[PDB]
Length: 204
Ligand SMILES: Nc1ncnc2c1ncn2[C@@H]1O[C@H](COP(=O)(O)OP(=O)(O)O)[C@@H](O)[C@H]1O
Image 1 (cartoon, rainbow, N blue to C red):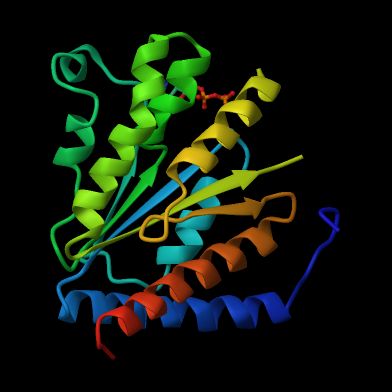
Image 2 (spheres, rainbow, N blue to C red; image 1 turned 90 degrees about the vertical axis):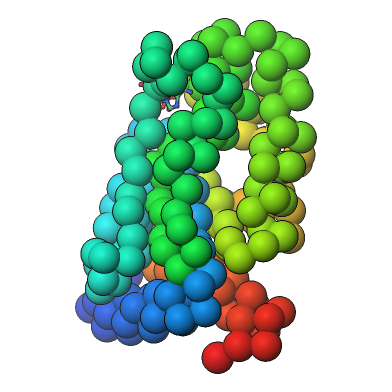
């Protein structure tokens, strides 16, 4: 159930998965392929928990995790994507975004920070940004975490999912009620995408 718990075997599985993640990093580094991981969800959904578990055994030299907050005034002097462009990883490196550019079609939309034209146009803008990256030597995965203006958020999220879920930049939905499930799920999904990419290129 969502009201389920798993244990002890969890701990063993986590370690294995975490080590598999280390191996992934080694691959990414060697083949100079960047990884951008996006975590979006409502507060208390377990984003940060998942992030911690994902990179526990990864070398800190290899990754940077970015907490994303509302744009400050100096950020508003440029286009909305610029902040993210500055925080992009170099090839071989991992960038994790706690919240992200998807803010445009989520919070900004709900709280009226973005005009309707602005947020309506954004899905395609975002898709085009991600494609510029994915066409080259970046991998992107996006994670949404749900725990049982909340209705308005679900509506916004769905449209996000419809318009911006793409093969090269998938949206993965994770049930967060059991934190352990979620942490395992995030690791499993991250690893699989990387393996499929390794297959797409002739690697490992
Ligand atoms: N572009 C953005 N505009 C405003 N807030 C943003 C933006 N990107 C991220 N945020 C974060 O979202 C917070 C607003 O609450 P939010 O998480 O969107 O809703 P909820 O609490 O209902 O899940 C801000 O305090 C900030 O941490």
